[PDB]
Image (cartoon, coloured by chain):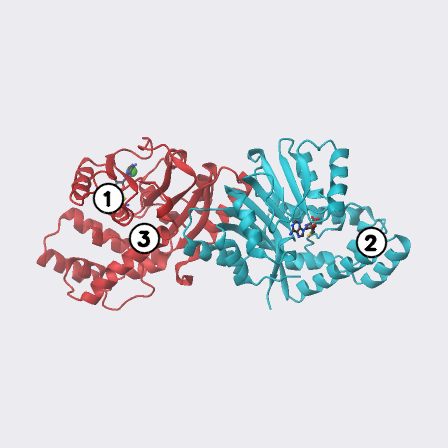
Chain colours: A cyan, B red
Amino acid sequence: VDESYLTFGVLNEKQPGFSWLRVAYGLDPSEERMRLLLHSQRALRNVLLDSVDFSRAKSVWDFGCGYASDIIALGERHSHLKLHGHTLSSEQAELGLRKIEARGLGGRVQVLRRDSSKDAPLESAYDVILGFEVATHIKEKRSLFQNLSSHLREGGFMLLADFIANSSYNVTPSQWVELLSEHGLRLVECVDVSQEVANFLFDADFDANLTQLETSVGISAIEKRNYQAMRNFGAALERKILSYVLFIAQKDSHVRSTYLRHINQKWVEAPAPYAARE
Amino acid sequence: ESYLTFGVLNEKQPGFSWLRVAYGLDPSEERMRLLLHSQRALRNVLLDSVDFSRAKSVWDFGCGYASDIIALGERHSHLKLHGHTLSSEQAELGLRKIEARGLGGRVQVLRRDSSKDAPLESAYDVILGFEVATHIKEKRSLFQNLSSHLREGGFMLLADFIANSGSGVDVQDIASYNVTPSQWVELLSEHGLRLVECVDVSQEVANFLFDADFDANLTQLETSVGISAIEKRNYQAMRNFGAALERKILSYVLFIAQKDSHVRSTYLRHINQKWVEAPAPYAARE
Ligand SMILES: Nc1ncnc2c1ncn2[C@@H]1O[C@H](CSCC[C@H](N)C(=O)O)[C@@H](O)[C@H]1O
Ligand SMILES: Nc1ncnc2c1ncn2[C@@H]1O[C@H](CSCC[C@H](N)C(=O)O)[C@@H](O)[C@H]1O
Ligand SMILES: [Cl-]
């Protein structure tokens, strides 16, 4: 089961019989529920990717790329792009290589075993940097954002999907403003998808389905634990303890540091609700 | 003349008369201080967005008597600043003001039509337009000329007007050709201009312009001082413009935009529509 089937998605309403886990693992045979799973996951990614004219981009850096599904998809869609992914796992980089070669993308899509908090990437200035739920797993956040912003083209896009702590490593609204502002990163938009991700994750039969999943399919103690966290994460979004937010930012060395903090505060504290889009 | 620009007051000030204070009929030093502070506060909404130490060239595409670019030139000694004006005599007066301050090298005023004529430089870091586009009918010609001479990532800073009703398309003398929210979205997006922010200062300018005794004050100005029919006409137009803001037939909006050739055109329209339809209230500012 490709990692992309196990990502978050956005659902506008909870669907009474929907279980993301049963559908992703093919345990639910409903063709409509499968198309809903895939659509919701594509819709979440699209909030970020629809901002970028990739026909005018040359290079993309995913600084926590997993099994490289996102850069593989972009590389298949835009044949001219060079895409570089970072992972901390030597084996995960090997699995990503295998997927990349099997799709003929080996010439321009790479996965490197590099620590994005401290290891420079291949290119001096990327057009787009992607991070789907990576920054919250990284302790040295200023070291990370220094490395990211140093290797981002002026005017280049940084596209993040990450969490805000409203009260692993949780980041408060005021901390996000400073992390972005200190590194010359100007938000174009924040989009709050908290409730819609909570809707996607809500599974009234979750514990039953997770057990049923573990006898039918084979899932490791690691995988089981990871899915338990996703369920708990949905509950935290429901309770508004956390927010799940999409950040569309650009490198901007020409805005004043006080004005940069003004406009980043506007978007971090008053993100656009997802339900008001087209 | 610069004492006759608009300012922002957060609430109506009883006994404050922009006309009495500007001319000196009111000898209050505190009120004179308020008048200048309010006019600076309006400019600063736009000017505070730009790190001018990292800018090299500024284009004021409708510069009046060059007051704005002279001030910027004296604050930032490295800046080149170019102003455009339609008349012949305004340029001459501006250049004399410029030369009287030793700014002749760096600051220039040209008689050029900004809707059609190319500026001196091919790519400015900042383009300024304080109530200029409202006097320019050929909006697409103008914005093509502005954007094609703006650096990638450069700032365009406009003080201008959104028409909210049919009556607000033309407010006599002060705001001649105002366009609707949807027309603003198209004018900006078609030319690769992305809003960072819109700031609505309508009510605070109406507060600045409010004078319950304007008529009596205007007659005193004619009695004590000498003003021409063209001056008298402009001052009544400013009073009536303040009333029009109170009726909300138009909005006085500050636009902070950047040239952005890399954002998708559908997304560019989304984020420009957000700011034109939901501008930040000036009052929410700290
Ligand atoms: N400091 C760091 N440098 C590089 N990669 C990191 C990292 N910290 C976490 N990661 C990577 O982030 C990934 C998991 S975080 C979430 C998964 C990822 N968004 C995806 O789409 O698959 C893993 O590949 C992990 O190696
Ligand atoms: N098409 C055009 N090209 C260049 N300047 C123009 C213009 N249309 C109007 N202007 C200029 O805009 C100015 C009037 S609008 C006045 C506002 C000006 N920013 C100021 O502070 O004084 C005049 O100088 C006029 O010549
Ligand atoms: Cl004109």
Q: Mark 1 near ligand 2 (CB under 8 Å)?
A: no
Q: Regarding mark 1 in the picture, which secondary structure is present there? A: loop
Q: Quadrant of ligand 3?
A: top left
Residue B229 versus residue B109 in the image, above or below: below
Q: Chain of mark 1?
A: B
Q: Which residue is mark 1?
A: B66
Q: Which residue is mark 2?
A: A22
Q: Are marks 1 and 2 in contact (CB under 8 Å)?
A: no
Viewer-nearest residue: A25 or A33: A25
Q: Is residue A195 left or right of residue A97?
A: left
Q: Please tell me which residue is depicted at 27% across the width and 42% down the height of the picture.
A: B63
Q: Which amino acid is tagged 3?
A: Arg
Viewer-nearest residue: A264 or B178: A264
Q: Chain of mark 3?
A: B
Q: Which amino acid is tagged 1?
A: Ala
Q: Position of residue B262 (x, y in %)?
A: 52, 38
In this view, the residue farthest toward the right is A215
- Quarter assignment of residue A135: bottom right
Q: Which residue is mark 3?
A: B43
- Labels 1, 2: one chain: no
Q: Position of residue B173 (x, y in %)?
A: 26, 46
Q: Quadrant of the C terminus of chain B?
A: bottom left
- Labels 3, 2: one chain: no
Query: Gap in Å between the C-alphas at discs 1 and 2?
Result: 69 Å
Q: Are marks 3 and 1 in contact (CB under 8 Å)?
A: no
